[PDB]
């Protein structure tokens, strides 16, 4: 990984030492990016419901993961399942129960810094992973995209700024997540995100996460070409809000 400072460095250290998993996957890769494209065809607002009990931003909730995934199976374009343990309270069991029970696309959200972690997603039943430009070297990014591509997964590559975009495009990314939050500091900038989004080739599938709770915020973002929306906190707190966001 890159040399990092502070909480991010700590989590990348946790992550290098994370025990891998052994399981045979008993389900297909259901492609998150294609389904998002499919919901653009039908003009259905395409929302990735995130399941996370905790965030470094101070969310701290208990709720049943299986009931949540099931409720979201009906309206979500896919699910994002936090598996990082220390800062998000996630776990691989959560992903495994979640993947066993629904048949919409599932993304594994963690801090992937080694191949066995992508192996962990596949064996647990996730259909794709998030990669962070910001914690990987360019050679690690490229080869971890190649490695996820080899289980037939198109990874979601997170960019926070323009230098991230240049590295992402160069390494071949076609599925890009644009974060308003910078993870190393927790600097939130929604104007920086808007600029960044206009620079992305028309040919990449674009996912946006702010801290989205409002329908107008989704609408603005769609106008700029954003294909799908990663929404966590507000749906952790009121799942049924999803209905009003999809309408
Ligand atoms: Ni991130």
Image (cartoon, helix red, strand yellow):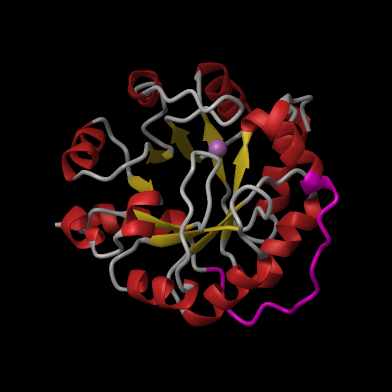
Would residue 47 appear left or right of 51 to someone viewing this image?
left
Q: Residue at x 16, y 39 (%)?
A: 216
Please determine whether, in this image, residue 211 is positioned above or below residue 34: above
Q: Is residue 125 visible?
A: no
Residue 8 in the figure: left or right of residue 14: left
The C terminus lies in quadrant? bottom left
- Given residues 87 and 197, the one toward you in this image is 87
In percent of width and height, residue 116 lies at: 80, 57
| Magenta-tinted stretch | 14-29
Q: Say if 166 sits above or below 1 in the image.
A: above
Left or right, residue 214 beside residue 134:
left
Q: Residue at x 39, y 18 (%)?
A: 192
In which quadrant will I find the N terminus? top right
User: Does the segment drawn in magenta span residue 16?
Assistant: yes
Where does residue 132 sit, x and y in percent of width and height? 62, 37
x, y percentage for residue 224? 26, 30
Q: Residue at x 60, y 57 (%)?
A: 153
Picture residue at 39% right of the left edge, 77% below the top: 70
Viewed as shown, does residue 231 lie left or right of 115? left
Q: Is residue 41 shown to the viewer in this render?
A: yes
**Front in this rendered view, residue 71 or 208:** 71
Q: Main secondary structure of the magenta part?
A: loop
Disc count in the image? 0
Magenta stretch: residue 36 in it?
no
Q: Residue 231 in the image: x percent, y percent?
A: 37, 49
Q: Ligand 1: which quarter?
A: top right
Of residues 62 and 129, which is closer to you in this image? 62
Q: Which picture quadrant has residue 133?
A: top right
* 188 lies above or below 102: above
């Amino acid at each position: 990984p890159r040399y990092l400072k502070g909480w991010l460095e700590d989590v990348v250290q946790l992550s290098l030492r994370r025990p891998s998993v052994r399981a045979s996957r008993q389900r297909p890769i259901i492609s998150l990016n294609e389904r998002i494209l499919e919901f653009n065809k039908r003009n259905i607002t395409a929302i990735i419901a995130e399941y996370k009990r905790k965030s470094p931003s101070g969310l701290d909730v208990e709720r049943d993961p299986i009931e949540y995934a099931k409720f979201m199976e009906r309206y979500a374009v896919g699910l994002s399942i936090l598996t990082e343990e220390k800062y998000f309270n996630g776990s691989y069991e959560t992903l495994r129960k979640i993947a066993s029970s629904v048949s919409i696309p599932i993304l594994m959200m963690d801090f992937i810094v080694k191949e066995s972690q992508i192996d962990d997603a596949y064996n647990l039943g996730a259909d794709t992973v998030l990669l962070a430009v910001k914690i990987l070297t360019e050679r690690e990014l490229e080869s971890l995209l190649e490695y996820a591509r080899s289980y037939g997964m198109e990874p979601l590559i997170e960019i926070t700024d323009e230098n991230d975009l240049d590295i992402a495009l160069r390494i071949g990314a076609r599925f890009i997540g644009i974060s308003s939050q910078d993870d190393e500091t927790l600097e939130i900038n929604k104007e920086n995100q808007r600029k960044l989004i206009s620079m992305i080739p028309s040919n990449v599938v674009k996912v946006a996460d702010s801290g989205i709770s409002e329908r107008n915020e989704i609408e603005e973002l769609r106008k700029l070409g954003v294909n799908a929306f990663l929404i966590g906190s507000s749906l952790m707190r009121n799942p049924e809000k999803i209905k009003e966001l999809i309408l």
